[PDB]
Amino acid sequence: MAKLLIMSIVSFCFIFLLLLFFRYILKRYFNYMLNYKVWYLTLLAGLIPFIPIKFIQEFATDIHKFNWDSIDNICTVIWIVLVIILSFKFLKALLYLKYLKKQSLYLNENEKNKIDTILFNHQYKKNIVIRKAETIQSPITFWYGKYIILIPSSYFKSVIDKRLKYIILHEYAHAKNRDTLHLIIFNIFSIIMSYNPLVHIVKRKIIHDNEVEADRFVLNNINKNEFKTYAESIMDSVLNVPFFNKNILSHSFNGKKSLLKRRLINIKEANLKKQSKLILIFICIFTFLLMVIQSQFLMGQSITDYNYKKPLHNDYQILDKSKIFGSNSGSFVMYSMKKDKYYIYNEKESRKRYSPNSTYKIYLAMFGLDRHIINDENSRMSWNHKHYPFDAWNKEQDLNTAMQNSVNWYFERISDQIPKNYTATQLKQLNYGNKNLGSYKSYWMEDSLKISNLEQVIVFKNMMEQNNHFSKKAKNQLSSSLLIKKNEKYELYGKTGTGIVNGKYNNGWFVGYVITNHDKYYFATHLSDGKPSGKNAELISEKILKEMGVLNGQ
Amino acid sequence: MAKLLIMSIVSFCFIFLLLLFFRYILKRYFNYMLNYKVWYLTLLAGLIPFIPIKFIQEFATDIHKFNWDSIDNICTVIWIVLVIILSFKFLKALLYLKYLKKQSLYLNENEKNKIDTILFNHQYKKNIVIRKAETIQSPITFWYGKYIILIPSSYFKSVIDKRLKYIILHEYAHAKNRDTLHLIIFNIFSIIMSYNPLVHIVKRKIIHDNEVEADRFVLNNINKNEFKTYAESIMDSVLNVPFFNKNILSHSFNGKKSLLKRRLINIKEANLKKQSKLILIFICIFTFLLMVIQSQFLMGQSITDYNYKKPLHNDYQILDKSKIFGSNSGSFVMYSMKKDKYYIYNEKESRKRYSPNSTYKIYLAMFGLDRHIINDENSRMSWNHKHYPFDAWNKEQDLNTAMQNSVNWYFERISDQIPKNYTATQLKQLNYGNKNLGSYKSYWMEDSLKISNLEQVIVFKNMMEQNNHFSKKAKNQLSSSLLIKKNEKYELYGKTGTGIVNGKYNNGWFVGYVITNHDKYYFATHLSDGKPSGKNAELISEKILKEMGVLNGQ
Ligand SMILES: [Zn+2]
Ligand SMILES: [Zn+2]
């Protein structure tokens, strides 16, 4: 529901921007102003969506969901705190102003005679207060319910400055316009709307425009001949003295910063000095070390998904089997144990590291067997009676079943029961791709562990013939669990399947080995285009393996 | 990979904030200054994460994914465009300067004599050039490796200004510091870093300091007696001339705005024009209409999930069956057709609405049958050839199969083929909870449609016995499809199962009716705590139903 504030922000902004648009045009073409009261409309807009005017078998299955409500709970607390802070700041300022008010003093007759001389031409209701002070360096004013104008006593002493009449007209207009009343009203609203920072932008614009209107007023009551003087006189007020911004809830002649002002202050002040160079030196040293620290951990690129770059250690040949892949564009690798030679189709692609998906079960099964979580005599794993997508997964499984029916459940348990260090050790000895087992129990499926087709051939070959860091028993049960098909030319062992995301097949694989009447082959097929299904990867591998003589005994 | 960009932002801000902090302290406590060149450190820090370093069935597994890649692709193009725009703007300013470079003239001997007198005791390297032009209302400077300093031709003749001396030193400082060059360099970089506003923001710190240092150079070479004069000279320029900001790439005495200046401008602009009141009126009207359009679409609420306070239209009593539920805290309702009475356990909970989940099928089957999408002679639905958690669903089903095995697949097709208006009309006639069927065919499973235990009792009872908006065929085939258990005392009809979210069992249900040798009983059991499984809801119901006479005929 915090989103509802976002919605009112958007509306608020639509209104704001439209109004802002007009403001620009009005001035740009006709020197027109938009009465700032219009801004109250955005404030109203700020609450639109806010106000809720909306006027047998047991079944069981898992649905993924995110809880975003705990976030709003956190945001709620923050908003509360912000209000507390903002409310306080308002109050602090207010208290001060009240305290000051209590110290103010009325004027004498001659002073009144002057003030009256200045404003009698307006013939207004004197329901405002003109007082003086011994505190403030320049005049200020604040509504409170009394409209009090405070002029430092020195300005009455220096009655002779003449320009006081400008000062009076200026403040008169501010009082007339109830500027500090509108300000505090808006401030309350802004305090409440802690969720929309734009409110602090519009208040600034309002304040500026209000000041402009006062200038017009004042000028409109002054003989133009004196405008030169006027401009100088007004300007002098921010030249002669420093400014302070304590009175955030009220109006004054010199209460805010500018870069110009900072310079002038800095100039007046005795600020010509030098420092030991050690300051910069240590800052740059420590900044550097931080940068180093960050560097130690901040890095990376698309390179994570890249291919295998090495030449081969055994003899090699490049293949062209593109006619077989057809619409299922992909890649393929085969290796002859007898010849110590690789045959590679579409090498640039066959080299790409891909998540192994279902083919990892070949290795995972081996790991479970070697670690004796599953053995030959008893290769079974338990389950938790939750429902699974295939009948094979709603049964307890042995290894033979689990491999051929790709039982993720079985294998989730196989992963769960094998130490990460073991898995990492064997991924390293096997030269298994990026050797990354992640932290996810099913790290091989559309996740962290990646291997190319070329690597998959090299790696499975190592699993059977070069890697002697597993017991023979593991190799043997795995072999039996991998048989797919046997006939008079070959024994085809392995496992196919596909990585599928949001219902689309993207990573079809078939990995294994072939015992033929003439040689022993290792292979890996991967499909990415067309319909890169499990069965298609299997069929593509077989058509190629037939052409290469693997499945023909040739 | 936008995340690397995010890392860049983070790295930058860390150094930036650290540095900013240090700078604050230096000035805040001792008016110490740190050479702005340190800001290059943030730019450099921003490059850290961009270093590309690391220093036998067919199966597939369907993984849900968020596509953030299309977003980065789009964002990349945008980033490119933003760079182009910035480059363009830079160039246009540069070309303007290019023009000026071919326009101004060097100075004569006496003017040189004046300047040399000014810098006589400074003994600065003079590999700089001072030139004059009618195009300059106030002096400007630009690097180009030449230190091009221009003055108004208008002051050439001002033999008594006594300001040039300040002008020269001010200009000198900027030339000396190669401030313009540094800004050019920074501009290259900020053009590149289109994604992180701080890269441009920081320039304003640089610019301010550049001016500060120039003031120091000036003051450092001035008999303090005249410091006041210098300050007056600054303001004189501020007041005396308008500024223009074409030279966004260089420095000048009068090239920028300020609030003060705006006011001074306004004083000097006698824009004595009338503005019709229609201006604000129409703007306010249009704004209102904008608000109206948003309003008719913007409205939020927590109300959707509010349960009801509605009294019943038949007799009732409140139950306490807490020793049956035990650790499986939940709720329960039963209704007697002959007594016209409800029995409500833990009504504070039984009156809450939950998605019907596994039991919606009871009602959906009545609808599918009434519309004859499934009928008695042919109650079947087609299959999409996808695999599901239950063996029973990996096929085409009839109603009797589908009801007993909770076949959402079958029922999802039923949902698609029942006009939403018919479903909704009867959800309303039956008082089916929030009567919300969403927009999804599977709306009953941890989704939009919600109903209480009390309401399910009411709904089924009406749907089969009191509601005459459904056919006899529907009533009869439904009753058959719902049978789950029976013996010589009762026939128990109904269904059970549980909605599970992120692996946790949240909404367990058992809903049904019993036909006995005595009466007709309608009921619903729901579990939320403990292990709120379907079977538990069913077992709890059976224990209660026996006590309530439902399963015995009492
Ligand atoms: Zn004012
Ligand atoms: Zn400067």
Image (cartoon, coloured by chain):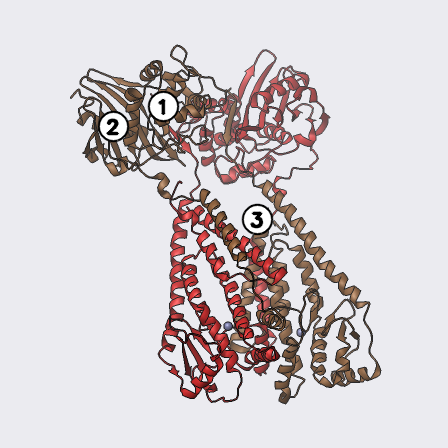
Chain colours: A brown, B red
Mark 3 or mark 2, which has the lower sequence index?
3
Rendering coords of residue B14 (x, y %): 52, 51
Query: On residue A363, which mark appears?
Result: 1
Q: Residue at x 53, y 86 (%)?
A: B161
- Which is more N-terminal, label 1 or label 2? 1
Q: Quadrant of ligand 1?
A: bottom right
Q: CA distance from mark 2 to mark 1?
A: 20 Å
Secondary element type, mark 3: helix
Q: Is residue B517 above or below residue B67?
A: above
Q: Is residue A294 left or right of residue A399?
A: right
- Which of discs 1 and 3 lies nearer the camera? The answer is 1
Mark 3 falls within which chain?
A: A
What is the three-letter code of the residue carrying label 3?
A: Lys
| Residue corresponding to mark 3 | A3
Q: Nearer the viewer, residue B217 or B135?
A: B217
The residue under label 2 is which amino acid type? Answer: Ser
- Circle 2 crowding by C-alpha within 10 Å: few under 14, some 14–19, many from 20: many
Q: Are marks 1 and 3 on the same chain?
A: yes
From the image, tell me which residue sits under label 2.
A541
- Taking the image as drawn, is residue A27 in sight? yes
Look at label 1 and name its amino acid: Tyr
Query: Can residue A35 be seen in the rendering of this structure?
Result: no
Residue B403 is tagged as none
Q: Position of residue B509 (x, y in %)?
A: 58, 26
In front: B533, or B96?
B96
